[PDB]
Image (tube, rainbow over all chains, first blue to last red; front, top):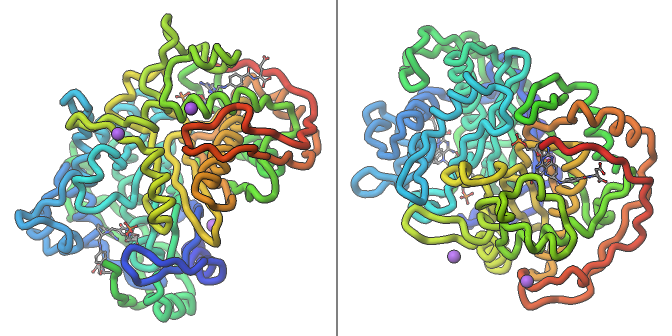
Length: 264
Length: 264
Ligand SMILES: Nc1nc(N)c2c(n1)CC[C@@H](CNc1ccc(C(=O)N[C@@H](CCC(=O)O)C(=O)O)cc1)N2Cc1cn([C@H]2C[C@H](O)[C@@H](COP(=O)(O)O)O2)c(=O)[nH]c1=O
Ligand SMILES: Nc1nc(N)c2c(n1)CC[C@@H](CNc1ccc(C(=O)N[C@@H](CCC(=O)O)C(=O)O)cc1)N2
Ligand SMILES: O=c1[nH]c(=O)n([C@H]2C[C@H](O)[C@@H](COP(=O)(O)O)O2)cc1CO
Ligand code: NA
Ligand code: NA
Ligand code: NA
């Protein structure tokens, strides 16, 4: 995507060399923002093939409030493998915080249900937020959330969303993270009878790993292609009733996939 | 400031009409980002007179963990009067969440001490974060947090900070928000023996109130003046031990103040 390839070139040209948690090393910038008008097309990177199978199941898993990777296994999804405990648990990561944020007094807040009701009853609200950054449970989480915080917004019948990503592996993570939240905006918009607006991506520590450089130079040599179109084939009874089969990406004609080793 | 006046003009050129909680009406955009290199000067708006005294005291109050306006009144600061209850209490807003975020298992997390220790011991960490968005306590707060989430970053011996402001009153609120976080970066950098880097401001619902329009255009007719310079005159033994008199602002030569009504 044009904005994505501009970010990748900016990190190369302007990033500072950092040592990181993994010992791999990165080039890093701090603070970036991109905007995708979702009526221009679904923002799925075209300069390498990105597989949505795993994205979609993961988002459906988040929405079910699930943090045990069994559901992912049942669908041959392995991306949470490293971090699950001997019983297949990750602790209270995204799904738990989205669906059952615990109050200090033993109650719970369903942030997804709250946002749905805010969009349907108070669409002008400036407080339509889902946060995974539960400070009091970070220690129990298998991994600290990268997509920390997102906010919805309604203007002129269009639903927009902004994601704050505290830490962004530009090569391996960001294509999938953009697609996940773009998919969620379409789902939310459908359940609230809204049109789709913008997906705004904001990054904190935005980096390229030092062993992703050959892959980065290859990708930057490729020209982007027109964006595909997301079709939702069925309107479920609620945001919690979608199925993998409900989604079709029409007209996705990407360049070949690019493999690179993940920093553990 | 150049960046601030460009934001005002963008809301005016690109914003849409929204009703709002307060009944006033706004012109708003969703998603914005701007940067202030703090080595260029202290980013206190010059195209109207802004009163740094309230900004400083409010920040010292936050850092104490206080959420009652009595301290502010001891120092003739009235900016929180409209939302306090009969006893001066705001509920568990910024200061409480910064210093003592309550967990479900009875603990409290001092996020300011946490990020100070991360900056001293693990400055490459990608999760040097303070959040005020405590979902489980929003209903106890007089106002939901506007400057909701911020992240620190270190490169080339300089401390940077990014704020996610989910809701921004551009004319009345934003000048105070920018200066407050810039001051905090200087204080943190002092305590960590770092130089100052960038303050990155990111906005969610970024709006001009309908009854701020004549004031906004008056300000836009003015040329920014040179940024003032912040001098800190002591190194306290901790981030919690600063005093109002430790700060001096040099070379602040603003255009006249512009009065506007706050939306309650
Ligand atoms: N959907 C999603 N994506 C994730 N990437 C992701 C998860 N779920 C959940 C967990 C973990 C999964 N880890 C993996 C990601 C990718 C592969 C992998 O090899 N994929 C292939 C094949 C895929 C396919 O076939 O379709 C391929 O893609 O080709 C393996 C494991 N993550 C977190 C995550 C991390 N990071 C960065 C920021 C920092 O570099 C560092 C954090 O470290 P720190 O705490 O110090 O900041 O990980 C992001 O940027 N975004 C993120 O979501
Ligand atoms: N809608 C809304 N709600 C909030 N709670 C909120 C904000 N906006 C924005 C920032 C913060 C509240 N801080 C302030 C900041 C400034 C003033 C103020 O009075 N400024 C004028 C004087 C006006 C006059 O004399 O008529 C000046 O600068 O001279 C009041 C409160 N929080
Ligand atoms: O620091 C601030 N900066 C700021 O701009 N505001 C403004 C944003 C909104 O106009 C208003 C909050 O109202 P609301 O929760 O509906 O967004 O106060 C409020 C605060 C309070 O800290
Ligand atoms: Na940038
Ligand atoms: Na504590
Ligand atoms: Na003190």
